[PDB]
Structures are given as structure tokens and as C-alpha cells.
Image (cartoon, rainbow, N blue to C red; front, side, top):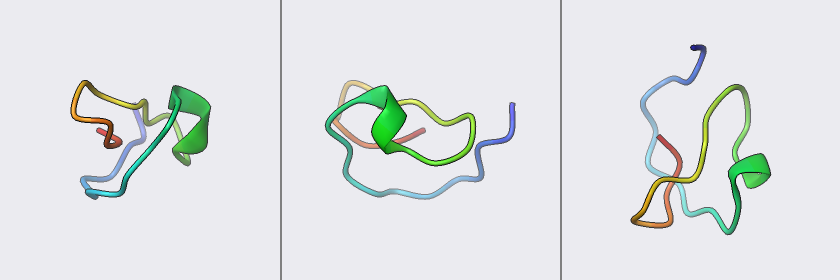
Amino acid sequence: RVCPRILMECKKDSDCLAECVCLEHGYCG
């Protein structure tokens, strides 16, 4: 559940660092 709250763009879930995932807005959780 390690996914600090940051708003960066993302194309796919792997694009985000840590355990974060790419949410509907196209940004990491």
C-alpha cells in the first residue's frame, strides 16, 4: 500500500513508481 499522495501523469499502471497504479484520470494514485 506504499503509494504516497502525488499527482503525476501516467500511461499505464507500471509507469507509476512504488505500489501506485494509474487511476481513471490518467494520473497515479
